[PDB]
């Protein structure tokens, strides 16, 4: 009935370095991102001061720059530069903690290109913890609050999808052929030979996260020296049952999935090439499959069949994107022109979830 | 001097080039082995062939051409055929498979493994040119090679040359006829290269030439050879002023100056009027007025578009043979009296005219008849936008479901490009609608 | 330059491959001893696609013959073209699969897969540029389905960016020579949907119908069915070996015909099929070929295209013909039969033309269709599979070799998902 999938876009603030590197022309860099409202975004606005001389030509007198590069994107949730991590945590992932504590599944996606600020958001600094830390902290506080009349159990897994193959991050020894997706008759999906862990507090959860991230399949010489070539899926299974209630053979189950997505890549950036072309191709295909799945799920018509089997990532989250499960998507974008083209692609990827035509 | 460098990319480009170089060799007396008998017979030293050939000391005339394809088949046909001894052995081939009809392979993955060699050979050719006029690029919009690799090559050439002219002679998809399912994608993705890196792009449709062959030449079963020969005649008409004498000579710069009003409106329509079989060569006068009238007939256009649904922005009439200027003036006055041929209010002059004394040469085994007169008309008009709009509709049918997109994104192409190109095309259409509007 | 590695697995695959190599050798002028005695220079121009040159001006096919019993190897060796193959490429065991998918995939094929892959690796690095692979087998059996799927998986792991074709013989509802065909077919389609770029589905029922009606044969044998399949196989690869006006390699057909990654199960067909004593009564021209390709009776997959819509078609012509005629004939087929073509693809027909027809014909054409009617085949298998799996009829023979019921459930679910995906693009929308 309602839109279970919600898209959140966050605009980062210029770094002092970038803020003084080429913005001096304003007194070359310019803020291609403009924010008007909690659901409104303008890409490449015509806000430059010496600009009348250009539309003196764009209008029908000299057809050299008649192209209009201003785009108008609408999203469910928008965060400006001034908003801090508390507002993002409250407005994107905090409600999901209810559903997982209620019994339903929940999903969080993190997407962006290099320099977009995704790391600061999901991970953050020790002084300014990210979204994951706040979610797990409130989850454990809720568990302690509900320690009476109910018992909760937390299981943690952390896998990665690389070249359409699953690879345990917490137990790197396991071979891929062993890691296989299995669909039970309970409409639950389990990956074989997963190294499940029982952390006791958010400190242990973060320690497991860094231990896994130490193993992630990265490669150097890309715009970032530690770019990710895989989709990292962290799964927190909450299994709970009444403590002093009916002692029956029934305990309720839920999962919180947190997926850090690899950024799309244009080989044109790559020159030497090799197996990295295969990595890029797999990443782009997986992102396309995920976009198709999300667009079909949002669309009331095409969802008679949703292409879950086009990629391992969508197959794993078959029962974590539909109507019952609540999905949120944090898409971190930069306002600097240095990342112009990439940002547009990011803004085009988020928009696909719901093609809200802003011409109206 | 007046050199021109021809670049033939893909199967369509190479086959059009086969026709073109057959025609040029016949025009200048050069034999397929590259030797000119007239040099030893008459004595030589009073001929102009440098526009398309380079002479060595031994008397061999090597064409100024660069044949490129990502598969060996068509070029291998060229190196085993009659003209094996004509071209320099450096005819470029990727030692791997083709682009498989997708822009990503021709641009990003498979096309980067010969671009250095192609640019090196273009360097070696241009260094031998003292008076280089421009590049003649032949390709097809609907092909993976002829879209991706031509885009990459023209990006590189614009970076390296910039000032030199660049002329495209491209095969555009027909409205109904097609020979691949992913033609709209490749052609839309080719909008950037033909809008920002070209200087005058000529578009041709196979269906239009098929209808011309049926109606005029009386050929119910034409193959691609006839299409290529007709395109070769058009290109010969364009470059005749750089090779032969005439009353009014029109080089590339004058032609572009007279035909391109703004930097973006450089997509004219070609028309060769006296396409006539030998049987119908008799029973017809083929005067200058008749041929000039035939140029403006919608049935004779080489793109499936109706000029009556648009306003002519400029016209260039390039005549060959026995043509006097007063006959051309009378024909142009007759055309201006006609009301169905509408001109924009801001081009009162309208017509550029060139005349050349060299009549067209007939290829043995060809379909065109021997005619004392000929004309090539190059018309900048607003009707061509229709030919784009149809193609855009096809794109909008496939991209809605993201069909065939995984092939492209799995070869180093971001998804957003598919939208971006479309937007560019839409912008171009708007410009073509905003120039025909009359002044206030 | 565009080298293909051919792998034969099982009785059906080995027999089709032997007939296919006879056909290709006749096409290229290679005699049974491996010597070239052709009449034109085009045969040797692209002989490297399917053959390797041996020292005495000999040509050894780049074939790999696989089985779990030596009977079919002995049959192929003693055949007319048995002496042309490399003896080291003959890889075989001694204990057969027994019409068991588990034996040829877990127990007895797993032992031989290392040798087969060693030979595949040897035949791959000897190529200047490897276009792809070419597997011939049947899904209704043991060693065929099992070892073919295992080799598919391991080659796909080793050569992820190369084409992998598959000429797989589907089981039929009427014709049934084996009782446990549904299990094997489901377990093999579970593997083909994930690790193949082109799967050319063939049915013995459709080939027998072609023999009885089109060819008017009285006593068809497996030689004739292999003849038809080999004709199609040669037609698919024609543009990699001969020049033409429009060239189309395997990857071009895959790009044009596969709108989404999982919809790569194609129905083949061969155009000029006529009975002897009825060839003088027809004019072999492009319209006749075009009318024969799109006829329901000419398909080799035992499906009615009228029960579905064509997602895509590919027509690969051979011979001297005009491109105008082919273009109008395809446009006429699409406009006249608009109900059998999807609306959200404007042109549904990839077209390729080659300049060299087969040996005794002035022209020919190969049809490769991707339609929703193929759905029916999978549906039929399910209608058998469930009927045998609700009761666990012949299941202990599989579970005894390490398999589980989870694999059967997974394969059934994947096949039903494929059926649903094909059904999605059928109704008007
Ligand atoms: C008088 C005449 O025209 O002779 C024809 C012929 O009569 C017909 C009936 C042939 C004939 O085919 C059959 O009888 C046949 C029987 C069962 C299954 C398949 C074919 C022919 O045998 C088949 C043979 O075909 C070839 O030679 C092709 O090159 C074919 N290769 C082989 O048949 C072959 C097999 C083993 C060893 C060497 C060659 C081929 C087809 C596709 C792609 C590559 C090659 C031809 C021309 C004829 C005969 C001889 C009677 C037909 O065959 C083909 C494949 O075109 C059957 O209907 C067609 C149309 C022909 O008119
Ligand atoms: N006029 C004309 N058009 C041709 C000719 N050959 C091919 N074409 C057109 O080219 C279009 C398809 O593009 P191709 O030329 O096949 O692409 P390609 O150059 O081979 O590039 P690849 O796909 O990578 O091999 C078809 O729609 C044909 O109409 C020709 O000889 N003359
Ligand atoms: N949303 C933000 N709010 C405040 N500072 C930010 C924000 N995003 C980025 N920054 C600052 O800018 C720096 C560069 O961005 P950073 O977050 O490091 O990119 P990233 O997340 O590593 N890129 P990627 O992982 O590819 O998405 C950060 O280290 C912060 O100092
Ligand atoms: N076309 C063809 N089909 C065959 C042949 N032999 C068997 N078949 C089919 O294949 C099935 C048997 O599979 P088979 O290949 O013998 O199993 P395998 O030995 O384990 O690979 C039967 O249902 C037959 O319909 C043959 O020679 N030609
Ligand atoms: Mg080609």
Image: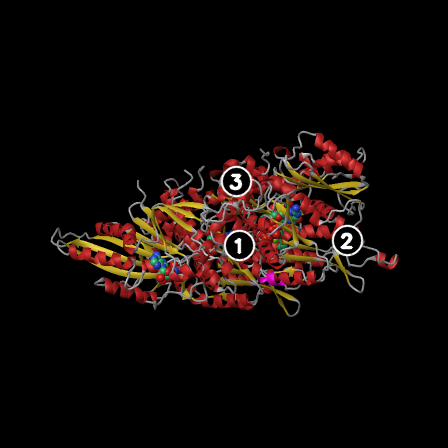
Number of residues whose C-alpha sits closer than 10 Å to that of mark 2, classed few (under 14), some (14–19) or many (20 or more): many
Q: Are marks 1 and 2 on the same chain?
A: yes
Q: Which residue is mark 2?
A: B25
- Earlier in the chain: of badge 3 and badge 1, it is 1
Judge whether B41 appears above or below B221 on screen. Answer: below
From which residue to which does the magenta span run?
B113-117
- Earlier in the chain: of badge 1 and badge 2, it is 2
Q: Nearer the viewer, residue C207 or B404?
A: B404
Extreme residue toward the bottom, this view: C55
Judge whether A352 appears above or below B36 on screen. Answer: above
> Which residue is painted at 67% across and 32% down in the image?
B341
Extreme residue toward the right, this view: B42
Subunit of mark 3? Answer: B
Spatial distance from mark 3 to mark 2, Cα to Cα?
A: 42 Å
> Which residue is painted at 36% across and 40% down in the image?
A300
Judge whether A92 appears above or below B321 on screen. Answer: below
Q: Position of residue B300 (x, y in %)?
A: 69, 37
Judge whether C360 appears above or below B58 on screen. Answer: above
Spatial distance from mark 1 to mark 2, Cα to Cα?
A: 36 Å
Does mark 2 have its CB less than 8 Å from ligand 2? Answer: no
In magenta stretch: residue C422: no
Residue C399 appears in the picture as rendered: no
Mark 3 residue element:
helix
Mark 2 residue element:
helix
Q: Which residue is mark 3?
A: B393
Give the total number of marks visible in the rendering: 3
Subunit of mark 1? Answer: B
Q: Position of residue B350 (x, y in %)?
A: 69, 38
Is residue A327 left or right of B305 when viewed as pictured? left
Q: Which residue is mark 1?
A: B104
Number of residues whose C-alpha sits closer than 10 Å to that of mark 1, classed few (under 14), some (14–19) or many (20 or more): many
């Amino acid at each position: 009935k309602q839109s279970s999938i919600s898209v959140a876009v966050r605009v980062r603030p210029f770094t002092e370095a970038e803020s003084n590197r080429l913005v001096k022309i304003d007194n070359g860099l310019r803020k291609i991102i403009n924010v008007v409202d909690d659901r409104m975004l303008i890409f490449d606005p015509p806000e430059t001061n010496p600009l009348t001389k250009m539309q003196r030509n764009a209008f029908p007198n000299s057809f050299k720059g008649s192209r209009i590069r201003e785009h108008r994107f609408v999203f469910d949730r928008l965060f400006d530069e001034d908003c801090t991590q508390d507002q993002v945590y409250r407005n994107t992932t905090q409600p999901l903690l209810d559903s997982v504590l209620d019994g339903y599944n929940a999903t969080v996606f993190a997407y962006g290109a290099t320099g977009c600020g995704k790391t600061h958001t999901i991970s953050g600094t020790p002084e300014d913890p990210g979204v994951i830390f706040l979610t797990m902290k409130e989850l454990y506080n809720r568990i302690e609050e509900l320690k009476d009349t109910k018992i909760i159990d937390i299981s943690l897994s952390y896998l990665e999808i690389y070249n359409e193959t699953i690879r345990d991050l917490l137990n790197p020894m396991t071979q891929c052929k062993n890691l296989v997706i299995r669909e039970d008759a309970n409409n639950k999906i389990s990956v074989s030979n997963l190294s499940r862990h029982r952390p006791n507090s958010v400190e242990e959860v973060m320690q497991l996260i860094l231990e896994g991230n130490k193993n992630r399949t990265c490669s150097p010489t890309e715009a970032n020296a530690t770019s990710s070539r895989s989709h990292a899926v962290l799964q927190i299974n909450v299994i709970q049952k009444d403590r002093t209630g009916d002692i029956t053979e029934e305990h309720t189950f839920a999962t919180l999935s947190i997926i850090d997505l690899a950024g799309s890549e244009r080989a044109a950036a790559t020159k030497n090439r090799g197996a990295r072309l295969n990595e890029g191709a797999n990443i782009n295909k997986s992102l396309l499959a995920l976009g198709n799945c999300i667009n079909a799920l949002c669309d009331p018509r095409r969802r008679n069949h949703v292409p879950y089997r086009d990629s391992k990532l969508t197959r794993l989250l078959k029962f974590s994107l539909g109507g019952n499960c609540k999905t949120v998507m944090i898409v971190c974008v930069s306002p600097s022109s240095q990342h112009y083209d990439e940002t547009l692609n990011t803004l085009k990827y988020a928009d696909r979830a719901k093609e809200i035509k802003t011409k109206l | 001097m007046r050199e021109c460098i021809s670049i033939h990319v893909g199967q369509a480009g190479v086959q059009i080039g086969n026709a073109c170089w057959e025609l040029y060799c016949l025009e200048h007396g050069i034999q397929p082995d590259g030797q000119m008998p007239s040099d030893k017979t008459i004595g030589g030293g009073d001929d102009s062939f440098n526009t398309f050939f380079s002479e060595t000391g031994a008397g061999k005339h090597v064409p100024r051409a660069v044949f490129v394809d990502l598969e060996p088949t068509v070029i291998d046909e060229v190196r085993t055929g009659t003209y094996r001894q004509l071209f320099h052995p450096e005819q470029l081939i990727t030692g791997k498979e083709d682009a498989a009809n997708n822009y990503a392979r021709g641009h990003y993955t498979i096309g980067k493994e010969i671009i250095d060699l192609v640019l090196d050979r273009i360097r070696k050719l241009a260094d031998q040119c003292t008076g280089l006029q421009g590049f003649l690029v032949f390709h097809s919009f609907g092909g993976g090679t002829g879209s991706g690799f031509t885009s990459l090559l023209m990006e590189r050439l614009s970076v390296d040359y910039g000032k030199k002219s660049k002329l495209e002679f491209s095969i555009y998809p027909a409205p109904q006829v097609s020979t691949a399912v992913v033609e709209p994608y490749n052609s839309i993705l080719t909008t950037h290269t033909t809008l920002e890196h070209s200087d005058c792009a000529f578009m041709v449709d196979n269906e239009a030439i098929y209808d011309i062959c049926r109606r005029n030449l009386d050929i119910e079963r034409p193959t691609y050879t006839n299409l290529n020969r007709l395109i070769s005649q058009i290109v010969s008409s364009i470059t005749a002023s750089l090779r032969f004498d005439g009353a009014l000579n029109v080089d590339l710069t004058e032609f572009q100056t007279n035909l391109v009003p703004y930097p973006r409106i450089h997509f004219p329509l070609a028309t060769y009027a006296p396409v006539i079989s030998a049987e119908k060569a008799y029973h017809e006068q083929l005067s200058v007025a008749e041929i000039t009238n035939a140029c403006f007939e919608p049935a004779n256009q080489m793109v499936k578009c109706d000029p009556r649904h648009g306003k002519y922005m400029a016209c260039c009439l390039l005549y060959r043979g026995d043509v006097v200027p007063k006959d051309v003036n009378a024909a142009i006055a007759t055309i201006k009296t006609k009301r169905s041929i509408q001109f924009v209010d801001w081009c009162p002059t309208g017509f550029k005219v060139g005349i050349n004394y060299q009549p067209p040469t007939v290829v043995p085994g060809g379909d065109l008849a021997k005619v004392q007169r000929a004309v090539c008309m190059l018309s900048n008009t607003t009707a061509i936008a229709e030919a784009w709009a149809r193609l855009d509709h096809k794109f909008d049918l496939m991209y809605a479901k993201r069909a065939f997109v995984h092939w492209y994104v799995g070869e180093g192409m971001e998804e957003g490009e598919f939208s971006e190109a479309r937007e560019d095309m839409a912008a171009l259409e708007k410009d073509y609608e905003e120039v025909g509007v009359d002044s206030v | 330059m565009r080298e293909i590695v051919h792998i034969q697995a099982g009785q059906c695959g080995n027999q089709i491959g032997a007939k296919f190599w006879e056909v290709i050798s006749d096409e290229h002028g290679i005699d049974p001893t491996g010597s070239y005695h052709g009449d034109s220079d085009l045969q040797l121009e692209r002989i490297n696609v399917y053959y390797n040159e041996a020292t005495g001006n000999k040509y050894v096919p780049r074939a790999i013959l696989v089985d779990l019993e030596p009977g079919t190897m002995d049959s192929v060796r003693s055949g007319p073209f048995g002496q042309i193959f490399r003896p080291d490429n003959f890889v075989f065991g001694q204990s057969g699969a027994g019409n068991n998918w588990a034996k040829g995939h877990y127990t007895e094929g797993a032992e031989l897969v290392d040798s087969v892959l060693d030979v595949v690796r040897k035949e791959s690095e000897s190529c200047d540029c490897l276009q792809g692979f070419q597997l011939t087998h049947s899904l209704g059996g043991g060693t065929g389905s099992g070892m073919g799927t295992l080799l598919i998986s391991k080659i796909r792991e080793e050569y992820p960016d190369r084409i992998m074709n598959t000429f797989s013989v589907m089981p039929s509802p009427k014709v049934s020579d084996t009782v446990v065909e549904p299990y094997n077919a489901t377990l093999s389609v579970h593997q083909l949907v994930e690790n193949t770029d082109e799967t050319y589905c063939i049915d013995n029922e459709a080939l027998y119908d072609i023999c009885f009606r089109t060819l008017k044969l009285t006593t068809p044998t497996y030689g004739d069915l292999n003849h038809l399949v080999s004709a199609t196989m040669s037609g698919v690869t024609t543009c990699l070996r001969f020049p033409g006006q429009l060239n189309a390699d395997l990857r071009k057909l895959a790009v044009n015909m596969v709108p989404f990654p999982r919809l790569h199960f194609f129905m083949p067909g061969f155009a000029p099929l006529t009975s002897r004593g009825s060839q003088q009564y027809r004019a072999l021209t492009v319209p006749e070929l075009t009318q024969q390709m799109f006829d329901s009776k000419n398909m080799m997959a035992a499906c009615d295209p009228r029960h579905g819509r064509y997602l895509t078609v590919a027509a690969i012509f051979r011979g001297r013909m005009s491109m105008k005629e082919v273009d109008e004939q395809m446009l006429n087929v699409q406009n006249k039969n608009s109900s059998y073509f999807v609306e959200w693809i404007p042109n549904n027909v990839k077209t390729a033309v080659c300049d060299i027809p087969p040996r005794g014909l002035k022209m020919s054409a190969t049809f490769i269709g991707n339609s929703t009617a193929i759905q029916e085949l999978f549906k039929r298998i399910s209608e058998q599979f469930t009927a045998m799996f609700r009761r666990k009829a012949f299941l202990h023979w599989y579970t005894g070799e390490g398999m589980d019921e989870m694999e059967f459930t997974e394969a059934e679910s994947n096949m039903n998902d494929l059926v649903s995906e094909y059904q999605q693009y059928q109704d008007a929308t």
